[PDB]
Length: 214
Length: 94
Length: 221
Ligand SMILES: [Zn+2]
Image 1: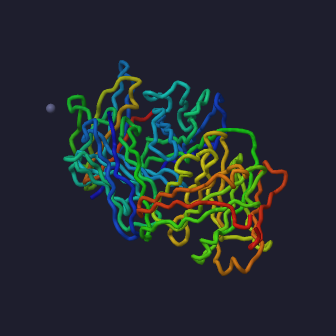
Image 2: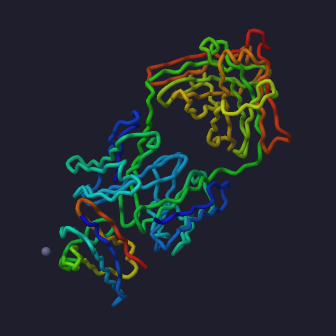
Image 3: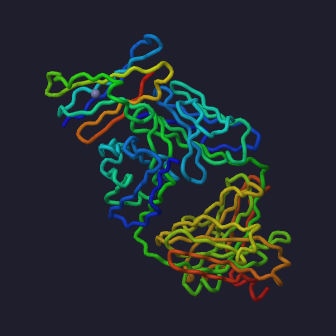
């Protein structure tokens, strides 16, 4: 089995910049390597084969190089259509094996999230479950920490979150976290808080409400 | 049923042309397909040479298939082996 | 001209079997090997195996030898990947591809396989009302929680498509119940909340559900 080590796993770049992705094979693969582009987990598209032969229709800004165990894909003058994921694959021996992939995202200035908190609606409380939602809006980079607190006690294991892909306008992320508890338990506590940590913030920001408060 | 060990070797460049030999060995039963592909597709048998399927003195068999290829076009070729409903593929080394 | 068209999304129960297809066109089907590949977000791309559609002879990744069965019907230009004894580990996107001279090309569009015991259920839609704790400067955030549905996907729009700027509809999370939940939010001016009506339009086609939930400030505000 050939193991393919692809680095880096993620990459932040701007339009016009040059980026390089490397794939290192665990044994000699004799230049039987191809590079593929993938956007949003859709059909992979062939860029380069035999390590350096550019495929038909592929822009000349894409450049494959390598031999033996060391291979790279270079994208000179990165264009808006190049943001997405890339992976290498070897065809020297079966089973065919793949690099772990490189996500190429749009670089921009650090932007702190604006934090919003939503109590459970009166409509939901009729169902016997309570969902408290925390929104972290329009931030960069992607790395952020949400910490829920109920009566100043840190919560763990009772929340789930999701992040949008980079926005088309401003290249930021947004994040939604949902704290779930029973209606019965929701009505036993008062203070519900969402503590957000992010490098754009001067210090961690807490957004909270008191149950029953306007 | 014993699966074949498949191995591809290449000769020195004669007049800018390499001879590639795909060998299957240590297999049973005797029925085997072994053929060269170019760009993923089987070549004509008239562009290839086959050895007989001969015993190796251990209850198993061995054979080979060869074809000539122009220098600089080696990565387009793949040996295809089929035996007992299994297949395997093997590109040209170096 | 060359095209590998796969079958659609699959929602299947654990312990059962399923067969997904890959229909080839624009070339001589029996001349090229068909390849199968599994993709999950967590653990990357994995090669399952190859088949020669001319003879039906297979080359499996040892990891899928008990799990996967590759077949081909050359009369209909179709290759098949069958799974036995389905588990949650099989939930993935599956691609077919074509073997060229020692590389893959002509990848299919992909087919999503979701293994679950859940039945089809429409979402409950709850308003995420604007308040003092969802204001930032002159901006107010509001939204809709689309909770406890199966299967994916749900679409959300705002004011029947008239409101799009500042809208963020998040990817769904799978709850321990086996049902999905997602939120859709929008940021608007705080001063518009007295005059402008805000309605999220939730469509869940699988369960034949369409919900229009007005989202407004709390009665005390
Ligand atoms: Zn003849």
